[PDB]
Length: 194
Length: 194
Ligand SMILES: CSc1nc(C(F)(F)F)cc(=O)n1C
Ligand SMILES: CSc1nc(C(F)(F)F)cc(=O)n1C
Ligand SMILES: [Cl-]
Ligand SMILES: [Mg+2]
Ligand SMILES: [Mg+2]
Ligand SMILES: [Mg+2]
Ligand SMILES: [Mg+2]
Image (tube, rainbow over all chains, first blue to last red; front, top):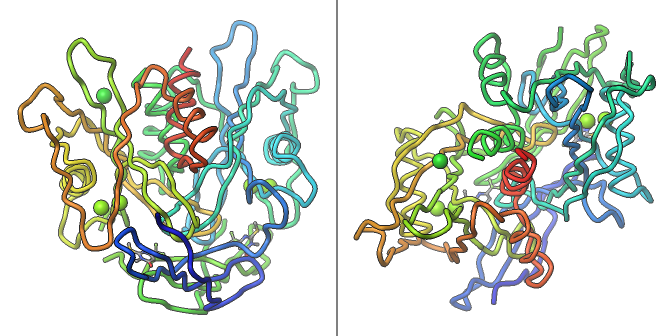
């Protein structure tokens, strides 16, 4: 029975805006919320994609391909799934394969594509598709993969065995100042709990 | 190689602020980033999210989730039980408290993540992911009494761990909900561990 009554702009940047949201609570009382949104969403089913890249090689354990980047909002290096915003007119699947090749150099194959999932729904309206992609690491195209970083993109590739992912993330967190992304950590936890 | 030079306040609300981050890019070039932060961090992290494993003998193991209207999203979301850590509260104690308030369940800590980032391209927000087991056969968890704070309105949805991804896909298909990216990520890995 809850719904939005109004969205009032508080502050609009080039990339991010702050809104005062007025909504109806389930007792029938109007309340407000401070809401973050991006300015970059057009007709896309979501802001962005994140790629779960499963690197497959004969006589290797499967790896999960991760990226390490400086994230200004965090003031530090973060370990994440490869990810980027969806270009206007682009499918989530094309954005996923394109961002994976740009950030890691790998040419993947689509396996599955999530519905739009919320990044931090108490804070923002931001959504992604989580796109699972396999990388045939036996293909010559995926032998010596070179990232194609865009202007101001600076990405390090970290491939960790699926069968030990959580302990290998713990060992990287123990060795330096860096944050693991919550989606990566949730995925590594589930691999342990299965 | 990369670091924060300065931060410029653009807009402060009660709960969230918008900053302009100046940072040194690895080439020796200074760059700007629009960054969101909470105003509420004093703590290991802003928040906890609880992975609650409901264990009842002769039943499938369930993951306990919550459905809430999220004003930034303009709709209903399915999430791990979660809230901000009170000043002076440990992440573990915040986890058991949030789980009790949102679900009525009384659980035991299994493990606690380090601080992990929610959306590091947009925000500095971090959480501890806290794995909790719930002895569902215990009297105290027979008729679980959820204690919602002012303006909290939370539905409990328990889904079998062994079919979690298909069950979440079903809810999105029929109920027009948004699944949280950490919940979806956990559900994917449970399928991918095979
Ligand atoms: C933790 S309560 C709250 N948090 C936020 C935000 F997440 F954006 F920081 C905005 C808001 O309006 N409230 C009531
Ligand atoms: C996707 S590029 C970008 N995104 C953001 C934000 F994520 F906050 F929306 C801010 C910013 O300055 N840039 C360059
Ligand atoms: Cl467990
Ligand atoms: Mg990216
Ligand atoms: Mg990119
Ligand atoms: Mg909550
Ligand atoms: Mg709460």
